[PDB]
Amino acid sequence: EQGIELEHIDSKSEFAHRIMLTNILRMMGCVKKQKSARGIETRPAQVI
Amino acid sequence: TRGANNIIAEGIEKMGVRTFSQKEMAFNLLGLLTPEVVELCQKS
Amino acid sequence: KDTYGFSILDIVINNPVNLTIHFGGEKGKRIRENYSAMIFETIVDGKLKTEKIFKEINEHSTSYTFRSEKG
Image (cartoon, rainbow over all chains, first blue to last red; front, top):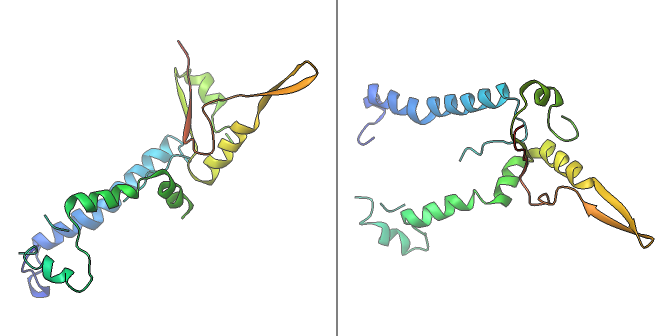
């Protein structure tokens, strides 16, 4: 994202925010759901 | 990290600040996957 | 599950060929210490020799896999 100030926040900015925050959180939630469904408590995934 | 933002990296380093390359930054990130740092992350 | 981190019910139901126990987190460390504690002791020449079960488990071990041919 270049040259997108507060007044320029638009579809591209919202999509980038989705990629970089919301879908990351969804991905960790999905890994959590898979591990819980398989009953895994002692093998955590390290989210860097 | 050095891959516009590179021409000034030398100037930022003249004041003691440290700038990393992609390899150095990857080394730092992989240092966080060591068993001891993994165990630390599991702790908290 | 509490002691060794495996389900005998799951083993009976599914009969997996291999089963991996993982030692991550506090519960994983507790299970690992439980795995390391058990030892087969033998009396040779009136001396109490100790043989550690699970050779491939130690303070730095992150998991242990049960190996079987068919199940």
